[PDB]
Each structure stands twice: as C-alpha cells, then as structure tokens.
Image 1 (spheres, each protein chain N blue to C red):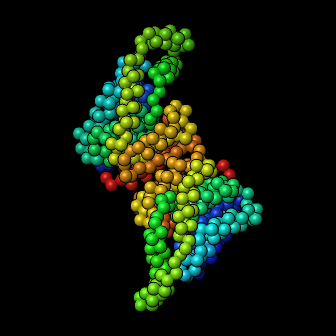
Image 2 (image 1 turned 180 degrees about the vertical axis):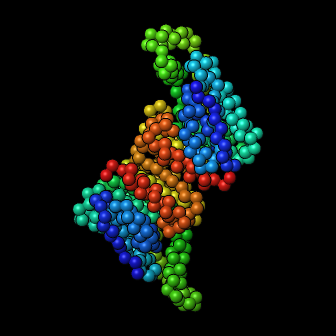
Image 3 (image 1 turned 90 degrees about the horizontal axis):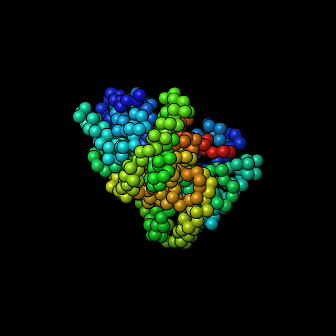
Length: 242
Length: 242
C-alpha cells in the first residue's frame, strides 16, 4: 500500500513524479539517494494510482496534473524557494509541462514518452497492469479471470485525454527553458526511445543534456543501472545555480 | 619540441589525434590516463605541427590526414586488432572520417567544428597561434612584430582545403556507424558549439552519446574539467564490445 513521501534534508528541493499505472515506490530509492546527498524530496501519488486498478479507470491527466501541482505547492508551502523536478515515464511528460508552468530549477525526464500510442495499445497496457495487480494480491487464476471480465465492462474514457496530454506537451517543448537532463533506456520496450531525441532537440533550454543507458529497461529507476542513474542525476542537480 | 607518443598497455588500443595548430602534448594527459586504465595509446603529430609556425603554412589537411592514417597503421603493424580513436577539435573531424574509412571500435570527438569559418577568420587564428608561439620563445615585442610582418608575406594556400575537409566530413556524417561519443564545451569560444548537435544528430551510429561541459573552454583536454572528461571517455570505451 504505497504512500506519498517527503524526505526532509537541505534547502534544495526535488519533486519526484511517477508514471502511468505506477506510484511513489517507483521513485523512492531515487528520493532516498537524493536525501542522503542533502536534497529534500517529495513524491505525491496520482489519483487512481496506488489503489486497486478499478479506481484508475475513471481518472485521467486532468486529475493527475492536480496531484503534480499540489506536489509542487506542498514543497513551496513547506518553505522551499527553488524546486527541481524529475519524472519517470509519463512523470517526465508532467515534469516538462511543470517546467513551462511554474518556476523550476532543473528538469530531469526519465524515459518519458513523446510518441502517441493508439487507445487500443494503451488499454492493453492497463489490462496487463490490472491482471498483474490482482496476481500480486494473491487471488487465484479463477478469481482473477472473473474480476478481469467485470473490469472490462467499464471502458476507460480517459485514454483520449492521455493522447491529448502527450500531444500538447510535445507541441509545447519549445516553451521549456529550464536546464534539462533527458534520461533514456536505449532498448526501451515500453515507449519509442527516439522520444528522448525529440525532447532533447525541441526544448529551448540553453543547458540541456541527454544520456542513454545501454543495459536498462523502461523503468530505469528499478533496473540494473540505478546506481549510475543516481550519480548522473546528482551530478546534474549539483551543476545548477540554485 | 613535442614528439609523437606510444604508451603500451593492453590489447585495447586508442589512437589520439590532436587539433589544428596543436600537437601531441594536447592529448598526452588523456593518453596517460587511458594507459593507467589498461588502454594502449598512440598519438602522432601532424606535418607542420610541433614545429615553428612558419612550417605550418606550407601544410594542409592532405598532409595531416597522412599522419592520421600512418598513426592508425602504426597500431595495426604492432598487432592491435581493435582500435578506437579520440580527436580534439580538427582531430575530431579526422576521427569521424577515419570512422568511415577503416575499422574503428569507437569514436570520441572533442569540440570538433562542423561550421565552415571564412578563410579570413581561420587565418586570424593562425596569426594568433604564431604570435603566442613566438611569445613563448621569449622574443621581445619588437622582434615578434618584425617576424609577424614577414610571416604575413606568405599566404597559407591550404585554408581552402581545410574548408573542404570540414564540408566533406559534414556531408558524410551519415556514413558514420561506429559507436560515437560527442564531447563539447558549452561555451566554446573558438568554434560554434552547436557543431556537437550536428554530429550527434546526423551520424547513423546505433550507439551515440553527447555530453556538454559547462565550465571548459575549447581546448577541453587542458582545462578544469579534464578529470571528469577522462572518466567519461574511459566509461564510454569500457561500454564497447571490444
């Protein structure tokens, strides 16, 4: 039962944003590493996430965006003047957007999608997520099946809005000016890795970096190169003015 | 009076190529570092280089390229099966060219120019190099001026061939497939730093990386971030199959 977290440390703050169907557990270790290096971190959980899959179906980017903004406000109200943001997958798309919406010290996108998938494909992914969750609950193949059939009676009408989010941020990359570090798994199995080149080339940021990880999979924060990832993000954050 | 160098270590070999008006001293610390990590290194010196400026004006890229090829051959003739190449400034242009001419395990370009400077600007560069060299010789301002007046009486007819080299390699970046690491000083004062983006985006290599250095000038090998540069190049070489 994942929960949002808030690792308090130095005056430099970093908002950590997870991806679609993910939760704060996907960016916790990164938060712990940054905390140890003196960076206070805050990771909210989007609505519909960190709960049974049935609750995800009726939420969309308009809801998750609120969670992102309130997460930023969380830190501000806590007194933190300058805030950086690192997002994983869809979290990276929100980081870019936040980057041209409110004051941001630096932006780190980690395997953020910049290609538009069809609703059919996105939904397939949601089905895998739901079935995998029910398996983790311990339920049997029999109960899973019955619950998945009920699950399918209710279509997810927010996938068109998810396509709209990606398209909108992609169309507004030229509004990004804050220092950005584009992180990407060279052999990403979930999104088109070329997404990293679109972000890196289209943002207007005078300070922009891109790094490819050759051994990692899509969820780079939980893969075999997380230690290098941590070091790279830390070095990037340390290079900012603050 | 600088000289070529050959630091014998293991079977992984790296050819180190210097830039226009430079010599092997410019890539020596990198050589020592790679040697200290087990990499055999060889650095030739281009004709017209490592000697008085008066000699430079009678040489051109057709000459220097022969020293680059003989450098590659030097390592082959010594039994080294796989060879990577790292070049500084113009050395990077030759590194890319070498990359699609003979078998190369990996390429590192460090502040390589991809924009064509006018012949006048290039010559201004040569004049500056000549003056500084004479200054380092301990000659008085008056003597330097007299020698510089003389110097100007001999045009350097090969600056047009230098433009040809850059245009030609730029036109053929799509022929580069070997793993490539583009290194670039963000605030390069000698060349247009955007050159790094042209190389990174136009080569065909499945494995390509680009990294910017925020506090280095053009001769990045001799500046304040060289220790980090060394580590990055080593990590990149280590990531190759070999």
